[PDB]
Amino acid sequence: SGVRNLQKQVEKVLRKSAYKIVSGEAESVEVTPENLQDFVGKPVFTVE
Amino acid sequence: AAKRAGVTCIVLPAENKKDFYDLAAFITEGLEVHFVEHYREIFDIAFP
């Protein structure tokens, strides 16, 4: 019910984007839903 | 630990099909995994 865990996720995604900037290839990361599993991995929950 | 003991099959909750695949491929060689969720599945992957 709290927002703390989503706060952890979006943090993680962003800093990984920073790693793609500072040395990596892209000069401007563009997250897309199809892209996402790359950055933050496989889905955790499914079977509510 | 299962690798050290010579295990050659293993059964996990389907919800962890994610984490098990993060492991480096050489760790996973020689096993034969069977992800499952409802218990009845397991009954048919042990006895018959």
Image (cartoon, coloured by chain):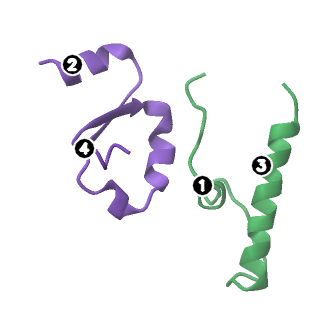
Chain colours: A green, B purple
Q: Are marks 1 and 3 on the same chain?
A: yes
Identify the subunit bearing mark 4: B
Q: Position of residue B29 (x, y in %)?
A: 27, 57
Q: CA distance from mark 2 to mark 3?
A: 38 Å
Q: Earlier in the sequence, mark 1 or mark 3?
A: 3
Q: Are marks 4 and 1 on the same chain?
A: no
For mark 3, give the secondary structure.
Answer: helix
Q: Are marks 2 and 1 on the same chain?
A: no
In this rendering, position of residue B48 left or right of residue B9: left
Which residue type carries mark 3? Gln
For mark 2, give the secondary structure.
Answer: helix
Q: Is residue B33 above or below residue A32?
A: above
Residue behind mark 2: B44
For residue B32, which numbered disc appears in the image?
A: 4
Residue behind mark 3: A9
Which residue type carries mark 2? Asp
Which residue type carries mark 1? Gln
In this rendering, position of residue A47 left or right of residue A17: left
Q: Position of residue B31 (x, y in %)?
A: 26, 48
Identify the subunit bearing mark 1: A
Q: Quadrant of residue A38?
A: bottom right
Q: Nearer the viewer, residue A47 or B44?
A: B44
For residue A37, which numbered disc appears in the image?
A: 1
Label 4 vs label 1, nearer the camera: 4
Identify the subunit bearing mark 2: B
Identify the subunit bearing mark 3: A
**Label 4 Cα neighbours within 10 Å, binned few <14 / some 14-19 / many ≥20:** few
Residue depicted at 74% across the width and 67% down the height:
A16
Q: CA distance from mark 2 to mark 4?
A: 15 Å
Q: Earlier in the sequence, mark 2 or mark 4?
A: 4
Pointers 2 and 3 in contact (CB under 8 A)? no
